[PDB]
Image (cartoon, coloured by chain):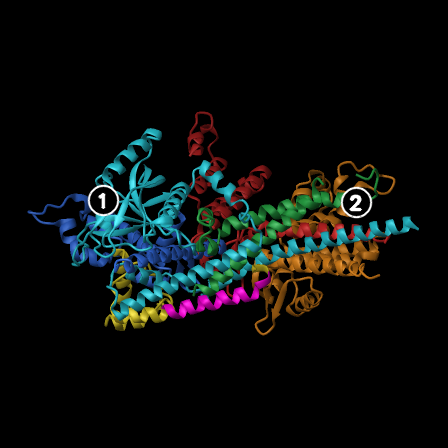
């Protein structure tokens, strides 16, 4: 029954080699880099209040972390899929 | 015709249970049961199935029990519990069709005008899509080849209603791999995609071997669709395509540059703070 | 004539005249012809408008099929001079009926719309995944064909 | 004849294949597109034509063997890439 | 910053104790042309009503401004050669005078080269009212200094622009700032193992 | 069209003369978009249209606007086109058309680029600036700022 049920969410090989959508991917990068800029703007303030008044996980640091993680993995996987498709498919 | 059939978890688990039930004592090449489903547009949705008393001769391929009255009253009672589900199609587990199967489909056509058969190879646990779907066809073939009572492939896929979806997910939870899987799952998915593409291309190789060598009849169809496939390859290295590819790849590279540089900056920021904190502790200890 | 204008293919205006002008403008007693294309000024103007419609359909066809063509080729196919062909193409493009660009220096007319890299590579990806789906469907039918021998 | 590897047809070879002058090749390709049996595109300033196909046709067993060879080259490349990626990405793949 | 400060107070200038209003507007138009790009020059100086109001009494600098804005380059050069004299006599503007006289030149060139991919040297020679050798030497110096995005084909005597496109300029700024940040990180590096 | 309808008005008829016919023919020039006849009207009526400051200023503005509109109308079917040809179509000399095109491109009101060495103007596709790179530059500059902030730190070691 295991991996008989799993075939339901099982990714297909064409789904694996699917190249997403370049216009949509560019829109995604466009939005995420802008969000990165707006996060770094207050990350600057957070590092400029390093003086340690009333020693206090909201906003800049981990949000920047998740943003860089998702952006980097999406861009890397899209480039790799595009490249693999370029060289293997002819 | 019928353009698609979607198969829910419940029928495939039911047929797995039926196969284990019969093979436990009466090990046989296949078991046969009846599916229940509904029609949207011209797509079919199948979520119910019950085992029916069935028997096949080993080699006579014309001798078979499928129980009429059992099928009828079992369907009646399944309608009593849930009346939406009407008889569509019949399932069997044999990895191969038989000369005897088209008679089974003709009997099932008495209960459904366009009854569709589904092969569910329970034993295989392999590359993908453990369900195959087939309809009955009888047409002149339009090319001078003799007509015959034939099975015709119809594309199939697995889809789940929400209750079946939570049910399947809960059981899969322990072995479940994450949906996002930032890098590991994506790279493994691409490698598995190359694996599947290689397997399909090797199957096409073996078919062409059998066709050229003559042990398999020329379908004329599909093989010319395969030739269309072969003419559909994009032929990269055409110059403007190369320019566009370089442009988009460079965009990805600058984006990943920004992400990596920010990662280095945050890494340094953690490092400096850790050094400051541990040095503060060391200075206070003295 | 109606089906010829319905055909998505060229017709030479000179050839069209040589084929059907006698029946069109003048005709005969058994095939009467109205004053739509008479020898008088209004009929002559309507005949010139017919020539304009012919070259319009020809430019439609070339835009449909050609990527780039020398204006000398367009002029030779429309039975006009390079000046007249350029003027008519400019008048038609300014009206934004179709897309066309004239590289007058290199002597070329480009009909294909410029393609941004995203659109080009999206077309590539669509071709690729269509090929992939076709391969999968082919394999399903392949197994079906092997599956007959049992 | 070709799996697109030389599908940019030159006018001369289609003209001599059709044993007709260079001036009729445009009409030939236009008729082919108009029937709906070819989806190529024509260039006239280089006289070469951008050819794409959508209409399949019959295969002889000769064509079957030719296809089997040209598909063998392709699947060999796929297997090459599969083991290459599996080798270079072993630690991440696992 | 001087141009923006002068522009902010052109209508509110009341510092008669320093110097008069017309001298202030002369300083303003002087600094604005060198400091501001053409759209800002149009919106904040060309359309600045009080500036034209006082320039109606001062045609000498009105010509110097409008010639640059209207691309009357020969008249612009004559007016710039004239204005260099007052720039030199100016008790405050003298120490930078050559620099100012230099900068406008490149700006002027940068304006004329804006609308052309390539052109004969004779065209700019006639436009600026100068000879081919003089302007050739001027572009030699300025391109050598990197102030202009063009190169000279002296065989045909044609200036040919090589201005980067939007994407290429973006990439060049990206890589340049990339090194200016990565060197800062590298110097910040070696905070490991003091 | 209203111009000819007002010169014939009951009150304006007593004032018919050079001044009225000057604006009549200027209006006629505007209707048929004839720059040559526009300048001819501006030339015959020197004392009627040039020395009148409001008339002169507005009419020069209108002539400039009409020249820009006609130039955009005629450049549209071209990607590369000789300046001589467009000068012939506009009936203005190349010495004037070239300066007008240079000023128009410089003001960014029209996308195109000249080359005198070939005597041509070129029409391009103006890619949409790609905000990704500007966001990239702002981000890296702000990371430079935070790097200076860490440089302010680490003096405490």
Chain coloured green in this rendering: A
Depth check: give the residue in front, E169 or A26. A26
Going by the image, does E47 lie left or right of C75?
A: right
- Residue E56 appears in the rendering: yes
Q: Residue B64: x, y in percent?
A: 23, 48
Mark 1 and mark 2 residues within 8 Å of each other at the beta carbon: no
- Residue E25 appears in the rendering: no
Chain coloured yellow in this rendering: D
Chain coloured red in this rendering: F
Chain coloured blue in this rendering: C
Q: Quadrant of residue B208?
A: bottom left
Range covered by the magenta-colored residues:
D71-91
Going by the image, does C14 lie left or right of F107?
A: left
Label number found at residue C42: 1
Residue sitting farthest toward the right: B286
Q: Residue at x 50, y 67 (%)?
A: D83
The N terminus of chain B appears in which quarter of the rendering?
Answer: top left
Chain coloured orange in this rendering: E
Q: Which residue is mark 2?
A: A48
Q: Residue B249: x, y in percent?
A: 55, 59
Going by the image, does E189 lie left or right of C95?
A: right
Give SS at disc 2.
Answer: helix
What shade does chain B have? Answer: cyan
């Amino acid at each position: 029954e295991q991996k008989m049920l799993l075939n339901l969410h099982k990714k297909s090989w064409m789904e694996g080699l699917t190249l997403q959508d370049y216009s949509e991917h560019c829109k995604h990068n466009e939005s995420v880099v802008k969000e990165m800029l707006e996060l770094a703007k207050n990350y600057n303030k957070a590092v400029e209040e390093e003086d340690k008044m009333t020693p206090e996980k909201q906003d800049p640091k981990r949000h920047l972390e998740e943003h860089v993680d998702v952006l980097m993995t999406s861009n890397i996987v899209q480039c790799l899929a595009a490249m693999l498709d370029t060289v293997v498919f002819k | 015709a019928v353009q698609k059939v979607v198969v829910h978890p419940l029928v495939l688990l039911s047929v797995v249970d039926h196969f284990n039930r019969i093979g436990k004592v009466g090990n046989q090449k296949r078991v046969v049961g009846v599916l229940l489903g509904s029609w949207q547009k011209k797509v079919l949705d199948v979520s119910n199935s019950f085992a029916v008393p069935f028997d096949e001769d080993d080699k006579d391929d014309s001798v078979w029990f499928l129980d009429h009255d059992y099928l009828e009253n079992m369907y009646g009672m399944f309608k009593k519990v849930n009346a939406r589900e009407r008889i569509v199609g019949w399932y069997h587990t044999g990895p191969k069709l038989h000369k005897n199967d088209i008679a089974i489909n003709e009997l099932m056509k008495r209960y459904c005008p366009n009854s569709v058969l589904v092969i569910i190879d329970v034993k295989p646990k392999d590359l993908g899509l453990p369900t195959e779907a087939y309809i009955s066809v009888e047409e002149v073939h339009d090319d001078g080849t003799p007509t015959s009572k034939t099975f015709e492939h119809v594309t199939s896929e697995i889809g789940a209603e929400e209750a079946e979806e939570v049910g399947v997910e809960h059981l899969l939870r322990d072995i479940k791999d994450t949906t996002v899987g930032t890098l590991s799952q994506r790279i493994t998915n691409q490698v598995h995609g190359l694996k599947g593409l290689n397997s399909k291309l090797l199957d096409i190789r073996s078919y062409l071997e059998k066709v050229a060598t003559g042990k398999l009849p020329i379908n004329h169809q599909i093989i010319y669709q395969l030739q269309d496939v072969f003419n559909l390859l994009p032929d990269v290295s055409l110059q403007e395509f190369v320019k566009a590819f370089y442009l988009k790849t460079n965009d990805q590279m600058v984006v990943v540059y920004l992400a990596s540089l920010i990662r280095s900056v945050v890494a340094l920021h953690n490092l400096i703070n850790n050094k400051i904190a541990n040095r503060d502790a060391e200075k206070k200890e003295g | 004539l109606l089906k010829l204008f319905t055909t998505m293919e060229l017709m030479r205006w000179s050839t069209l005249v040589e084929d059907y002008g006698m029946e069109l403008r003048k005709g005969s007693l058994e095939s009467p012809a109205t004053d739509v294309f008479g020898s008088t000024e209004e009929g002559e103007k309507r005949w010139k408008d017919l020539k304009n419609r012919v070259v319009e359909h020809n430019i439609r066809i070339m835009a449909k099929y050609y990527t780039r063509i020398t204006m000398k080729r367009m002029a030779q196919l429309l039975d006009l001079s390079v000046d007249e062909s350029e003027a008519f193409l400019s008048n038609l493009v300014v009206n934004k009926t179709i897309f066309a660009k004239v590289d007058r220096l290199a002597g070329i007319i480009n009909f294909q719309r410029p393609k941004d890299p995203n659109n080009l590579l999206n077309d590539w990806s669509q071709k690729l995944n269509s090929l992939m789906s076709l391969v999968n469907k082919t394999t399903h039918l392949i197994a079906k064909e092997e599956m007959i021998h049992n | 004849t070709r799996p697109a590897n030389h599908r940019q047809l030159t006018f001369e070879e289609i003209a001599k294949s059709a044993k007709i002058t260079v001036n009729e090749v445009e009409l030939l390709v236009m008729k082919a597109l108009s029937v709906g049996l070819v989806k190529g595109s024509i260039d006239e300033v280089d006289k070469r034509v951008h050819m794409t196909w959508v209409q399949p046709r019959v295969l002889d067993l000769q064509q079957i063997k030719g296809m089997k060879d040209r598909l063998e080259f392709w699947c060999t490349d796929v297997k090459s890439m599969e083991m290459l990626v599996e080798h270079q990405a072993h630690d991440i793949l696992t | 910053q001087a141009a923006e400060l002068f522009l902010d107070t052109v209508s509110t200038f009341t510092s008669y104790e320093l110097m008069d209003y017309k001298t202030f507007v002369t300083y303003t138009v002087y600094v604005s042309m060198i400091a501001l790009e053409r759209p800002d020059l149009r919106e904040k100086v060309i359309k600045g009503a009080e500036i034209l109001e006082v320039l109606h009494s001062l045609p000498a600098v009105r010509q110097y401004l409008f010639s640059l804005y209207e691309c009357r380059y020969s008249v612009f050069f004559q007016s710039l050669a004239v204005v260099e004299q007052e720039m030199k006599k100016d008790w405050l503007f003298a120490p930078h005078y050559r620099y100012y006289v230099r900068e406008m030149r490149i700006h002027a060139y940068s304006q004329l080269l804006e609308s052309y991919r390539s052109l004969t040297l004779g065209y700019m020679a006639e436009a600026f009212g100068v000879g081919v050798e003089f302007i050739d030497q001027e572009l030699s110096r300025f391109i050598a200094a990197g102030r202009l995005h063009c190169k000279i084909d002296k065989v045909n005597e044609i200036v040919e622009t090589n201005r980067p496109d939007s994407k290429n300029w973006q990439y060049q700024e990206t890589i340049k700032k990339g090194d200016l940040l990565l060197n800062r990180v590298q110097k910040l590096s070696r905070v490991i193992n003091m | 069209e209203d111009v000819q309808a007002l010169v014939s008005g009951k009150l304006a008829l007593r004032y018919a003369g050079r001044q009225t016919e000057a604006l009549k023919c200027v209006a006629q020039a505007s209707k048929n978009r004839s720059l040559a006849d526009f300048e001819k009207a501006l030339t015959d009526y020197r004392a009627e249209l040039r020395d009148d400051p409001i008339i002169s200023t507005h009419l020069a503005k209108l002539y400039d606007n009409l020249l820009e509109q006609n130039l955009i109308r005629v450049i549209e079917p071209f990607s590369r086109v000789q300046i001589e040809h467009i000068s012939s179509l506009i009936k203005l000399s190349k010495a004037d058309v070239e300066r007008k095109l240079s000023q128009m491109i410089l003001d960014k009101k029209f996308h195109g680029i000249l080359d005198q060495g070939e005597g041509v103007l070129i029409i391009f596709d103006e890619p949409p600036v790609d905000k990704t790179y500007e966001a990239a530059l702002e981000t890296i500059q702000n990371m430079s700022k935070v790097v200076d902030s860490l440089y302010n730190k680490a003096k405490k070691l």
